[PDB]
Amino acid sequence: MAKVEQVLSLEPQHELKFRGPFTDVVTTNLKLGNPTDRNVCFKVKTTAPRRYCVRSNSGIIDAGASINVSVMLQPFDYDPNEKSKHKFMVQSMFAPTDTSDMEAVWKEAKPEDLMDSKLRCVFEL
Image (cartoon, rainbow, N blue to C red):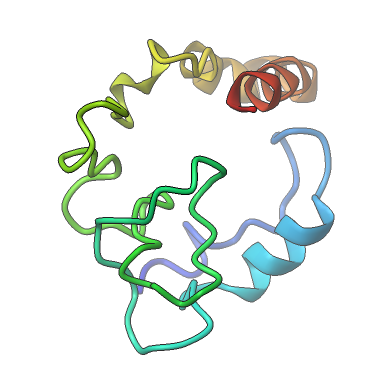
């Protein structure tokens, strides 16, 4: 668990993308914890090769650990996947232009998010 109010309080849409996604707002706000459908846990690390974004729908909650902060060791956990070459703070090289956008998100407001959001969405593929 974590600061339900400080960290999980995602409802204040102020500054972020543009508005509240349909699936994300509900799924994110609804799933303020267990990100799986089956099994009892929070996260593990290793995941399955989907190349579409850790879904963790199968309830391989052990698979849905690299979702972000859920991890306990590292937000990247790219250990077993050197070919894929991953990293969370370092990810700005792989593409994530949003890294510089982090400060710009609140500084520039939505206008900056819309640009970096559309940019990351297209780059992510």
